[PDB]
Image 1 (cartoon, chains in turn purple, cyan):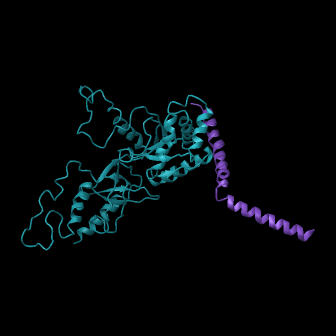
Image 2 (tube, each protein chain N blue to C red):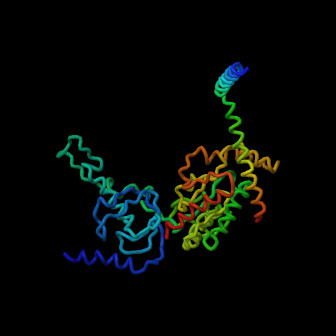
Length: 57
Length: 324
């Protein structure tokens, strides 16, 4: 029960790591990476537009 | 010969009694000439080897060969600067170091055709352009804000309005912000002896827009006599290509927005009415991005108003102490 569970967890973790390292070559992480910064600058530029309107002319 | 010793301290004494002597004019230099190689200076010592595109602001008129000015480095001191005629005169002397400086080659042909250097090999020729080594610049270098999109596009309008807001508050009593409408690109260094002196010429230039492209220079020079930074919002300056060699030579700030996809998002924030020049901004940003920075002396890379204000204020404050 404990040794067998350890073996199962180790094999599954190794397989998951291999699949992760094979799918990282495609670059699926880049799409998630590029999505975060595109959202960080979004509100950082929209608030600039918003408050500059209130400083009025 | 004790005469040289007497005149050695004469220049220093006059230049030290008054520490609050105002600056008269300013001049840019672009010649990498080592002033220490030649020991020709009124005061014995080693001069400053000024680099190209260095802003020298004159404040004295000593003689016709050398003058007195100041540089643009923090805690600046008093040094010597050669006259453009003196610099032009010594420019020809540099080529005299070589065996020949003209048509007659020394390819093992000596004593047959001496070919003394004519006026062609001297500085008399090359009068088609005759660019002086020294260029006249205002005492205070202006500032031009370019980007991140079309000037006056309701998105750039809100962009620099906040930037102009904090600038006129933090620098209160120290800044002068004005808006202009006339053209600025149609202005070169020298196109005629008397360009547009009279408005009753009735020619191809009488009805054109030349009495505003030039008249904004010396008018703003008087405003620059206070040595205060000047920023405008004209709808003409969209690339520093024409501002790199103009008389103004102002301060350009890079205000890029990083990704080009975000630009569409702020465009769609207001929805429609952005189709007038929407395709332009698809390339207008990229116009000042694919080109090398070079022109932008300082670059603003911040996605928020708060730290963007501190970036501009950081550069202005340090540059403020350079010419003082």
